[PDB]
Length: 108
Length: 373
Length: 65
Figure 1 (cartoon, rainbow over the protein chains, first blue to last red):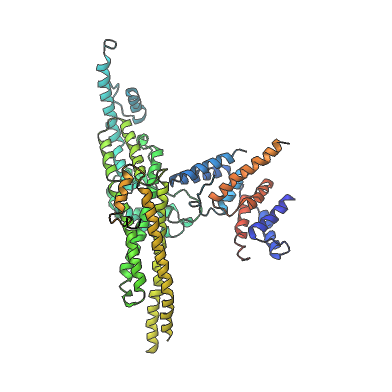
Figure 2 (cartoon, rainbow over the protein chains, first blue to last red):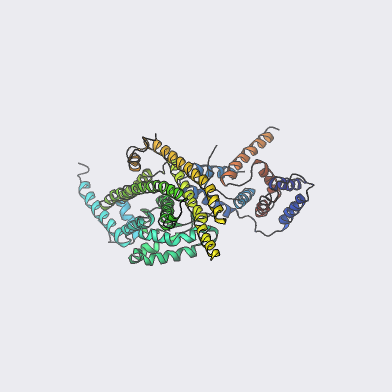
């Protein structure tokens, strides 16, 4: 119930389709749910996600980005304390990754 | 110290001469110094010959500190077309063999198989983004008894300095490609009365980049890997303890971190230095952005001559439209670069006591930035 | 009660942690869209399934340009 409204709002936000009476909204939604029900991936391996997180930290340390390395270790260690964790992490990881070298600018 | 040395000599090296040999009527000052002498001297000898500590250091300068130069340029020269293509379709299979062609061509081929075996490729910390030029790294594996002098935490320093001196030696080659484009193309553009201005403006702007990428790159040569190498070579060549090797090795790495811009305080200076890495790849594109229009038309003009065997007046006209925008753009780029390098120098003056202070006098003799202050 | 309202505060704090994680990985997501993705991950789904869709609609917003 909540999940259906969630997939609606994801189409609205991500695709920029704020009118549900657009046929493109319903086509993107049908695409979304059909992709969701096409089970084709293995389940998330928490250990591989952990290894990837550590490797991101090492890449930060290698490039002498000390504030981003300290931030990265700090945020990942706080988040991993109270499955879905590794899911969201992997999700973000594959989603763009784009300027992982850039965009440091650690405000907090 | 003595008991640790003789226990290490049994449990690790496994080469044994069996039973290696007022206070309380004073036998201590007689026994202990002789024992200390014999034990430590044998331990140093057997570690530098049975597992060869020194030959690894010489290939840690040539390979990891990139100080060889012949291998390093010819390797990267053969490695350019791979790195220009994005790194998701690049693997170790294509790394090790082009390394091998470089190795058989260069001075590396004569050397011992141990140090050559211990150089092998690695991928730089694989993460999506398709950064083709960034994905390459050397992993030097130490798994002997000498691992204790070449521990994994100071190899990380080797990796970091290798990374910075990968970026810089990439940019230098981009720059000399610009300089090569000048000496190849411009003897064809002497037949242009209008592009002469903008190409000449690029000639003038380029030499400041060349200069900035050759003053830093002689400070990095002759004070970062020539003085540091010497003082380290002294402090290894005399040293008469395992501790004495290790505790000079560590601070040699730290001192080179202080000489370059990779300290926690000199991050601000490193940002200024990265802003010169912006402009060089910018100017590289602009130089070819000339030729893809400018050189392109003259062949078309030749074919227009073959037609005859009013159109081209408009090609003159659209160029007299195009030239001022490109020239003024180049002007603003020049201003921007000079201003940010002045901002680099003004923070540079008081950072460290001597090392970074000397760099100010290297990068400016002319005192252009006393007359542009 | 109170600790049930301290928990809604501690989830918003963890969400701000995720907001910095979102930008240092450089995702296109922000506070609004990731709020949807969290509830979806509560219901259970492949993250590789959600991400391919988001990779599609972020590039199918240029068919709505």
